[PDB]
Amino acid sequence: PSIKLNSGYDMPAVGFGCWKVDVDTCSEQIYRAIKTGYRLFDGAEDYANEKLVGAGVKKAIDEGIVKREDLFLTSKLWNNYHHPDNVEKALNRTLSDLQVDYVDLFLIHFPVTFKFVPLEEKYPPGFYCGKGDNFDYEDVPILETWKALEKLVKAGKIRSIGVSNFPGALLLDLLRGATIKPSVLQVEHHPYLQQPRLIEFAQSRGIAVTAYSSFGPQSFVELNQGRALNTSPLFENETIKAIAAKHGKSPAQVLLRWSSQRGIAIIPKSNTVPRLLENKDVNSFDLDEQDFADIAKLDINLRFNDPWDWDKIPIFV
Ligand SMILES: NC(=O)c1ccc[n+]([C@@H]2O[C@H](COP(=O)([O-])OP(=O)(O)OC[C@H]3O[C@@H](n4cnc5c(N)ncnc54)[C@H](OP(=O)(O)O)[C@@H]3O)[C@@H](O)[C@H]2O)c1
């Protein structure tokens, strides 16, 4: 099952999330997921594993299990790299780590502009902005970054371009300046942060929405985030359990189906082989209108991935 992007390419509707994949088994896991049937891999410069991902894919291509053209590789431009002189440096490093000639989707990871740090100096940079333990920022409007991305599509290094973690007003302004329109909007999306109007906006413009953190706080419990600890797991939620029992499906299948059935692409992080199988078809069943209505009541605007936490960066205020 596939989503036709406005660029003309098809994006697999269910993918494999590469954030915080155990580093010692990362290449094996990618290979294994490809062999299990996953065709989209959601990666990023910031996840620090693009070499590992690229070896997984190398192996599966060499052993004949898949062709390059059957895979959909996503990556994301990190925040130090928005200046138009530096966009291509970061993309070239992603292409070399992945060992490919083009990437299928290249996203602006965040509408946040860290001071550039040369790649030989520190890669990937994280929060380092070339000034000690201090944040430092540069004045590069989004549209400058976007125009640099558009040249990289024209040069055949990227097929489709998009954005991650953009609010509505910012996306709307980007649409006014874009020649190639954004193909994808990738945002945090689970029942505790539903943002229904944002999704409605993006879909009405023909922009495919990718949900991340479909399991909500669970991904952030790994990092000991205070907010995530302190949140009741979605898996134990009384409504999610009623709905699971009603359809004979697991909580996790209900949480993923809630998005996939609304045409929203999913990219769950799938650590074990049964999870790999379970997460790859939740499209075995339909939620009904009463189900959506009961899940809609869980929305509390609880956001786990917020740059306000990093440095009071006002992306979501
Ligand atoms: N800013 C961005 O654009 C951004 C930010 C975050 C994520 N992402 C992307 O979206 C992807 C997915 O989001 P995520 O990594 O936050 O986590 P997620 O997919 O919400 O949650 C992953 C966690 O759920 C548990 N899990 C997975 N499948 C399960 C199942 N079938 N049953 C029960 N538990 C299950 C695992 O927890 P345990 O192993 O702890 O049991 C795993 O750590 C990322 O990997 C990344 O590619 C993008």
Image (cartoon, grey):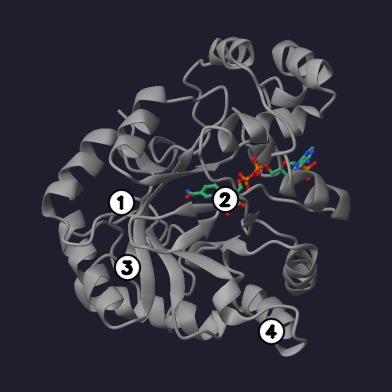
* Most foreground residue, 17 or 179: 179
Q: Nearer the viewer, mark 4 or mark 3?
A: 4
Residue type at the position of mark 2: Ala
Q: CA distance from mark 4 to mark 1?
A: 35 Å
Where's the C terminus, which quadrant? Answer: top left
Q: CA distance from mark 3 to mark 1?
A: 10 Å
**Mark 2 closeness class: few <14, some 14–19, many ≥20 residues within 10 Å:** many
Q: Nearer the viewer, mark 2 or mark 1?
A: 2
| Residue 284: x %, y % from top left | 75, 37
Q: Which residue is mark 1?
A: 112
Q: Earlier in the sequence, mark 3 or mark 1?
A: 3
Q: CA distance from mark 2 to mark 1?
A: 27 Å
The reply to whether residue 111 is in sight is yes
The dot on residue 123 is none
* Most foreground residue, 73 or 48: 73
Dot 1: element: loop
The dot on residue 61 is 4
Residue occupying the point 69% across, 50% down: 269
Pointers 4 and 3 in contact (C-beta within 8 Å): no
Residue occupying the point 44% across, 37% down: 306
| Residue 249: x %, y % from top left | 82, 28
Q: Nearer the viewer, mark 4 or mark 1?
A: 4
Dot 3: element: helix
| Residue 47: x %, y % from top left | 56, 62
- Quadrant in the picture for residue 29: bottom right
Q: CA distance from mark 4 to mark 3?
A: 30 Å
The dot on residue 81 is 3
**Mark 4 closeness class: few <14, some 14–19, many ≥20 residues within 10 Å:** some
**Mark 3 closeness class: few <14, some 14–19, many ≥20 residues within 10 Å:** many
- Tell which quarter ligand 1 is in: top right
Q: Earlier in the sequence, mark 4 or mark 3?
A: 4
